[PDB]
Amino acid sequence: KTFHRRVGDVRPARRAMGPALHRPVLLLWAIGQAVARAPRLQPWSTTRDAVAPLMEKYGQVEDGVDGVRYPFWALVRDDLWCVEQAEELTLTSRGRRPTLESLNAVDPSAGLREDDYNLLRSQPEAAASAAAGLIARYFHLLPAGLLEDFGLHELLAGRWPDALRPLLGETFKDRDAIWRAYGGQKMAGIGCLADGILSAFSDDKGPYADGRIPDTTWIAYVGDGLSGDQKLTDGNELMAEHQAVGRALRYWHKPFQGQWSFETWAVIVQRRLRWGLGEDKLPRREFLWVLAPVPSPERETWPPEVLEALEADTGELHDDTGDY
DNA sequence: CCCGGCCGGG
DNA sequence: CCCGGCCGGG
């Protein structure tokens, strides 16, 4: 329901050649519009040639013009968009987005939801997170290009990810108690909060212990399969996804009979396979995600030693199940 | 060229 | 089962 949620729920499926940026590109522009006090609903014709150039540069699509058709209809059933004069459009391919002719012929004014147009105009902070969300989840390298073009530069200048929540160091008693505040799931240590940003949870088993790998800057985090050989699925897949592109994630830590707290952003810098003990207490094959903390998601902020280490990493699983 | 059916991921 | 961008063939 919560606009914050729904924008977070916008996860395009993982096609082979990346996921489809069409739907985020639109939402990003549409926030840039509401920030720039543009009109709530706008006609198809005008939106089309306004977004299409962005879609070509920033959604790495060939025909930006065509591109817009899909999200322009689709985003409605993501409960974020709305389209007056729906009935009048003539549809194709069973229920899917209608024909280019009915779009050009009817020139339907489409735009953002009611409450959402109000919320963005009235509260910049909510507008700030949402573009920070997408900016993080889907772009996250921020080539100088889009800052200005999408909106936005004025909105998120300085440190963009400032707008995201939680803040660093925020503290909660339960795993549950985090969930009330940020959603996602109590569950695997690997997951995404309502905002659609990945979060990894480290529950310390012993006092005067934490995950730091000795004689090193980094943190050893264990894949989230609970009792037998772990699999590149769910949480582990998510890690591998982030690892590929060099995207960062929230590292949560509970000291031990201590409260959870959002201790740092971190980036996967190595993926390792190890023997370890299940919850069942028998040996098993498990993932070792090696994390390097960083100040924020903004690459500009990352120290060189981290950058070297991603450069250096092959991206490939290292199987140590041959000697331990 | 832009209907459609076709992919293939949830 | 479901749908959203892909891409064939009219």
Image (cartoon, coloured by chain):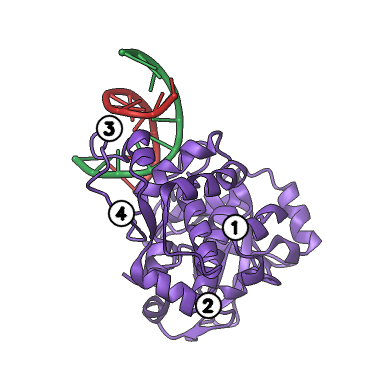
Chain colours: A purple, B red, C green
Distance from Cα at disc 3 to Cα at disc 2:
40 Å
Answer yes or no: is residue A224 visible: yes
Q: Which mark is residue A150?
A: 1
* Crowd around label 3: few <14 · some 14–19 · many ≥20 (10 Å): few
Q: Chain of mark 1?
A: A
Q: Please tell me which residue lies in front, A23 or A266.
A: A23
* Crowd around label 1: few <14 · some 14–19 · many ≥20 (10 Å): many
Q: Position of residue B5 (x, y in %)?
A: 27, 23
Location of mark 2 (residue): A125
Location of mark 4 (residue): A77
Q: Amino acid at mark 2?
A: Glu
Q: Quadrant of residue A195?
A: bottom left
Location of mark 3 (residue): A93
Mark 2 or mark 4: whose residue is earlier in sequence: 4
Q: Is residue A105 above or below residue A138?
A: above
Mark 3 or mark 4: whose residue is earlier in sequence: 4
Mark 1 or mark 3: whose residue is earlier in sequence: 3
Q: Quadrant of residue A117?
A: bottom left
